[PDB]
Amino acid sequence: QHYDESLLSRYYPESLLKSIKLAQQTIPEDTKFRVSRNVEFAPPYLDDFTKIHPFWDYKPGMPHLHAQEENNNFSIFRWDQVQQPLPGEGNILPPGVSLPNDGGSKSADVAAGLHKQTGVDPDYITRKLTMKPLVMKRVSNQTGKGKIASFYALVVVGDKNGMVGLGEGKSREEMSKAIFKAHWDAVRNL
Amino acid sequence: ADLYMHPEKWKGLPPQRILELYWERMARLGSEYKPNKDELNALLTTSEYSNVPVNDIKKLYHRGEQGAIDINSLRPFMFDELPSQAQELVAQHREQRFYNRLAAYELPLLAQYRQEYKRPSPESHPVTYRYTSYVGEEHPNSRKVVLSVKTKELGLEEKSLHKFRILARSRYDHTTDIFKMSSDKFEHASQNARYLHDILQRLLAESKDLTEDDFSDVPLDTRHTIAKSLRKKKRDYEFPEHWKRPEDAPKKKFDIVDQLLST
Amino acid sequence: FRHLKTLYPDIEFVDLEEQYRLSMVEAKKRRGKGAPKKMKK
Amino acid sequence: NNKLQHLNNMNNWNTQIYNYNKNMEIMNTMNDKLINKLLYKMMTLKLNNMNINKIIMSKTINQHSLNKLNIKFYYYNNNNNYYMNMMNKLMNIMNNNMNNNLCNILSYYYKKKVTIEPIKLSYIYLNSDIFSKYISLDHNISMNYINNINNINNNKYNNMINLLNNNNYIGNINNIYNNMTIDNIPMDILMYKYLVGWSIVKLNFI
Amino acid sequence: GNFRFPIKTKLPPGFINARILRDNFKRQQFKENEILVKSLKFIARNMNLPTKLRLEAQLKLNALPNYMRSTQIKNRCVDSGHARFVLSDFRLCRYQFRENALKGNLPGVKKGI
Amino acid sequence: TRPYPVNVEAVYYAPLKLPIKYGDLVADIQLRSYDNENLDFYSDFILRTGYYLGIPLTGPKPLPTRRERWTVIKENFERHTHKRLIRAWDTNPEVLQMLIAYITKHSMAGVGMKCNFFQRSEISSAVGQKVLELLDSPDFKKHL
RNA sequence: ACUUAAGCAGUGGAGCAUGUUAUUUAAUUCGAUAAUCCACGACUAACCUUACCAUAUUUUGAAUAUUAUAAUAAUUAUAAUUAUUAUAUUACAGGCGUUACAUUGUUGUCUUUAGUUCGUGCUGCAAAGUUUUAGAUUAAGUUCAUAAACGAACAAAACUCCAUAUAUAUAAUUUUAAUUAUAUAUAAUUUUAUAUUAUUUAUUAAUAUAAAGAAAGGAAUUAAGACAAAUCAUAAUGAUCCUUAUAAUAUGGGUAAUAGACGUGCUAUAAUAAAAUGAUAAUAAAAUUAUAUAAAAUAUAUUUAAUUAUAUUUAAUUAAUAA
Ligand SMILES: [Mg+2]
Ligand SMILES: [Mg+2]
Ligand SMILES: [Mg+2]
Ligand SMILES: [Mg+2]
Ligand SMILES: [Mg+2]
């Protein structure tokens, strides 16, 4: 609709005021606006476009296709950094990150997985239980394409106060993963 | 605003301003850059603003990268940046916002240059010239000009008009009564416009001349128009008039709702 | 690339292809596989 | 229908141009290729010896407009206040030098105004071209995206039905978009935001 | 001594081989001598003029070197120098055209559907 | 809540078009591009510019798309030239000049233009030069 | 289950065109050879193309860099410096030289792709196995069932895009083909109600009948093996070789020669089939025209005209407009 001059003056910059005046006298008040279908000229959100958002708007002085600056008036003289920093928090984290060091050993993983899968107490596992590997070997399997090697570990865990368990673990990738699986199984077999 | 170019005026400025002016002068000058007294003295003051010793800034000013050297790959992702493709989408949206702001607050300022359309009076402005302009291109067809006129509006009597049509030959179309000429021989379009206008004056002058001219007994030739029309499809037919039966047309039906809404 | 040294004295541009060609010539030079000297007219 | 949720088919082509004079279009394509190769050659910079920096940049995007050309490209690099490093000098000669900057020479080359737009990428796995040139030397995300898009759609729906319950022009613009804003809509609706897969060079961004 | 051809011709800005260089020479010399060749052909083919002038024009046409003939210009790929299967819409052989279309170097080209 | 004047509102809607009073066709603007999104966006911007300049513009008439095809021996490649048309009516030549200059100033990538201008108005030899010179030369003049 | 066997439609003995082979040639540029058969790229080879033959003819040559003399400018002060431009300057450039000179990249040909790893869980002391199932269904992975197995990632499918049918917008119906054009959007993998026969018997298939339907086709999109390659003209790098020659230019010739041999096509061998004619012009689509296209007209073959081919002359159109 149409607004009086002062009401816009308080709510808008002075330079934009003359544009709004010419728009007011240019567009009839009885105008009917029909939404476009094929081409969406406007943004999905609502904006008065009066202020420049550093991320969502072209940086002042940055050269680009629609640079309205005089060709030798660009104000970008240090190119070391990324010119337009991220908005909001400054970060683009997903809804839940899972990076314990970058999010914006055997005993610990064993304890956590065991508490998750069976309800065993992590603290008891980490503090009281002690593991010694008993058997560590490499076992092979023939196959039509070739020979496949795997690592077998047999470990014994115990709190030295009457609880003892035996665990066996297999891993084609590495012996450490086999020891991890053996520790897991031994904790399960206490 | 000519602060960067003259070395004299760095004194008293905010530290970031001295630093930005220093960067500006160095970047703009490039190879022609040379050390200056006042820029160094101003830079001496910038030691407090950032973590730099005074001799260190002297050294860095004097000998660039190497002075500083004398004094990463596959890094973890901090979720502080976008991919290139997402940045392309953000650039698209930046362009969209630029155009939206432009339409919002500068296009309303182009109404001050409106002017009313003084229609060229149809009878006394009968000749239409077509000029073409390929914007942002060096296209040879930008030199073509087309002069077209409906032959009736030409000021001519029956014998003179018949002579005009006879001498037009293939340039005249009897069905549409249009005389059209195309000129692209000269380099510019203005030269072709002058050429077409002069040929029109010659044609008109010698058509209006009937003193020693006897082209009344020559029938108008239309074989070129016949061929041109023969190379097009025709939809001349129309639904027979007597076949129409308006009796079966839909009859609008009374609905009291709009009657009471409007009265 | 030849023109760059004239245009931008401060910046020192390394064209990798010419460096590779020169190093290859040196490698053939080291083993005595270099081209025979062109006959002087 | 939205420029934050899709990539323009124009952006597929490196040289995006249309000229009525097809010969000029072919000439512009050839010029884009040659200038891209030259830009590639200029990306290595040594200071004396044992200081050989190698900037890895993707292929150039030549945006041809009626009155201007814009050469957009992404690049990777790697007391800093008081001096200039080689890459900064390179960019400043791309655009900022007063006398013989590169864009003026390219303008004389193309016979139209030219600008160059380098953009820094702080990582190497944010662009397939840069990643390949360097090494030469998710269901939760989708669920959140679809549900949030539904949230914006239903929010506009709620605003419109409320405005109706209180031609096709309905009412003031603010009520139509009462809560929709720059803070919430744009970043949420953007696509290709995260790298969800890779195979060393094909990088899948979703 | 310094250059293969009688007249100095500037080097093409892209891929170079011997046949591309010969093509460029003939192209540029055709540019320079087009008007002269056309005038000679006019004087030779104009039956209004005396027969002696026509024969003189024909003999002068025969005397011209090969790098002035219009027919001798052949379109070659600007990326590999091949002379066959050259598409004039891009001045590329079918293989280079294929690779450039796949990589997106050619404006507007796409895969068929 | 916050006042939003008519200019900002008009951005969020289809471009307004002025009615044609007389019917004189002063300018035909043909936009062609190899993609359509930039094409239609630029057409919409031209419509807004024409409205604010007082120019009655009909609209972007879709014209037949041209298809160029190539075969690689058996891979098929093709290029689509999309073409739009905008016509201007009942306005002075100077206003057309302002329109064209402004929209050229803020053009979009990959879109080419042609502007045909209709101006209603009142009723009122390198080879040849060379041939004359050769005929004067002492290799042809010696045969007279 | 490729492929075969069957049914149908053909083609198939001659001439020419176009390839390969043999032979000849100064060259007839290049391609295969471990016993079925196979040397076989042409989006146009008179010159150029061109790579081959003959005869002359060029020697840092096509680029990068070095070190020097000449002119041009810019500055300082004729000289100093910078650059540019020539002439030399030698590393070399160059090479359609070599695969009996190799390795990647790829280019294709064939097979397998409801399958391969990983994570847990379970069985066995263990190497290992992951079980019924070596299941059912379809025309086929298209679909189910079971069971110590269940997951995620790719792949497949869905999905996507064409075509089709509609809706909105756009076009001042003279750029008119509104029967059209191109943007957005919707639609289907069809949905149902019964009858009969089978059925793991219903909340299932085969059909058939009825009802709402415009709805009936298509392409692309992944990896793993294995073979073949140098017209690998689908390239790069390296190895080796020539450097008055295997590099480079010009004139002409050849790639078109014919005893033959085999492929590929065109024209024929007559009446279910050829020829002539058919102006208010029976009826299309997709293209192309600034390195163009060429309308109508006049003239000659030629003859009242028509047709057909050239000649003269360029009308419009650089294009939803004219050709
Ligand atoms: Mg030719
Ligand atoms: Mg020859
Ligand atoms: Mg030949
Ligand atoms: Mg070599
Ligand atoms: Mg050779």
Image (cartoon, coloured by chain):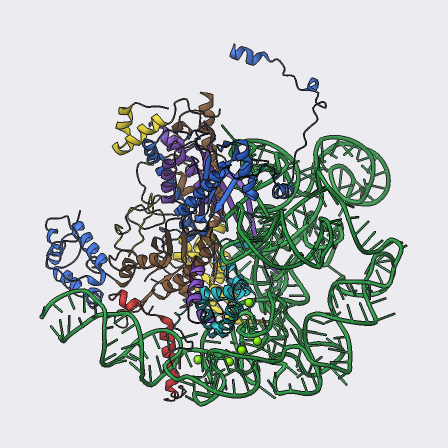
Q: Residue B106, percent across and down?
A: 33, 36
Image position of F57 (left or right of G76): right
Residue at position x 18%, y 52% in the image: B21
Task: State the image quarter where residue D57 is shown.
Answer: bottom left
Q: Which chain is brown?
A: D
Q: Nearer the viewer, residue D161 or F19?
A: F19
Give the drawing colour for chain F: purple
Q: Residue C29, percent across and down?
A: 37, 85
Q: Nearer the viewer, residue A96 or E29?
A: E29
Task: State the image quarter where residue C37 is shown.
Answer: bottom left
Give the drawing colour for chain E: cyan
Q: Nearer the viewer, residue G290 or F79?
A: G290
Residue F83 visible somewhere in the drawing: yes
Q: Which chain is green?
A: G
Q: Residue G118, percent across and down?
A: 53, 61
Q: Quadrant of ligand 1?
A: bottom right
**Image: E43 above or below B99:** below
Q: Residue B139, percent across and down?
A: 44, 51
Q: Which chain is blue?
A: B
Residue at position x 37%, y 32% in the image: F8
Give the drawing colour for chain A: yellow
Give the drawing colour for chain C: red
Residue D128 visible somewhere in the drawing: no
Q: Nearer the viewer, residue G61 or B227?
A: B227
Image position of B99 (left or right of B154): left
